[PDB]
Amino acid sequence: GAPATVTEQGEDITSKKDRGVLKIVKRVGNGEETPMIGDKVYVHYKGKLSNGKKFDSSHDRNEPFVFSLGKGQVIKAWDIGVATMKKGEIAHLLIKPEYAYGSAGSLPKIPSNATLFFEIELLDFKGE
Ligand SMILES: COc1cc2cc(c1OC)OCCn1cc(nn1)CCCOC(=O)[C@@H]1CCCCN1C(=O)[C@H]2C1CCCCC1
């Protein structure tokens, strides 16, 4: 599946090179710019536990997911991964627990030591 393909082919985009955040570009975006810290970012996404036991989508509200990059409004893996994306890009991310919810998890929704997968479309970003 998509998650295994990321395990096998996915670029390690962590600073520490600990394979905590693996990325595949699935559709190339436009222009050179990628968002900066503080930028307002607009995305569509689908997400799941790698266990496929819980599945979440912005599509479920028909409306984009909006957050400020690098403020830790989202898990660390997103601040890291969406920062590498161009406008219009779709990427797959596979995420170890250290860059998601950790040993504590986020129960009852997310268990301890959970690996997460997302598909993310970067719709737009705009400055603070
Ligand atoms: C841990 O709780 C949740 C996890 C997730 C979605 C959740 C959620 O309930 C609060 O509700 C959807 C609405 N939403 C999104 C956020 N806050 N609420 C952003 C901060 C938390 O989410 C994150 O940082 C990441 C990245 C941005 C999209 C959402 N996300 C998630 O971790 C998802 C998970 C749901 C279960 C399957 C994996 C993804």
Image (spheres, rainbow, N blue to C red):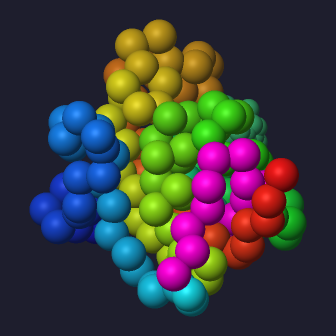
- Residue 112 appears in which quarter of the rendering? top left
Foreground of the two, 15 or 88? 15
| In this view, 93 is above or below 91 | above
Identify the residue at horizontal 45%, vertical 70% (top origin). Answer: 91
Q: Where, quadrant-wise, is the N terminus in this rendering?
A: bottom left
Q: Measured from the top left, where is residue 99 in percent x and y?
A: 41, 32
Identify the residue at horizontal 46%, vertical 86% (top origin). Answer: 28
Q: Is residue 39 magenta?
A: yes
Foreground of the two, 85 or 39? 39
Tell me which segment is drawn in magenta. 32-44
Q: Measured from the top left, where is residue 23 in percent x and y?
A: 33, 61
Q: Measured from the top left, where is residue 127 in percent x and y?
A: 80, 59
Foreground of the two, 53 or 82? 82
Foreground of the two, 107 or 89? 89
Judged left or right of residue 85, residue 39 is: right
Judged left or right of residue 19, residue 54 is: right
Q: Measured from the top left, where is residue 2 in percent x and y?
A: 32, 67
Instruction: Please tell me in which quarter of the rendered image ligand 1 is found.
Output: top right
Identify the residue at horizontal 40%, vertical 80% (top origin). Answer: 26
Q: Would residue 14 be seen by someone viewing this image from the given angle?
A: yes
Judged left or right of residue 101, residue 60 is: right
Identify the residue at horizontal 68%, vertical 58% (top origin). Answer: 57
Q: Which residue is most to the top?
A: 104
Q: How many marks?
A: 0
Q: Would residue 118 be seen by someone viewing this image from the given angle?
A: no
| In this view, 83 is above or below 113 | below
Q: Main secondary structure of the magenta part?
A: loop
| In this view, 69 is above or below 122 | above
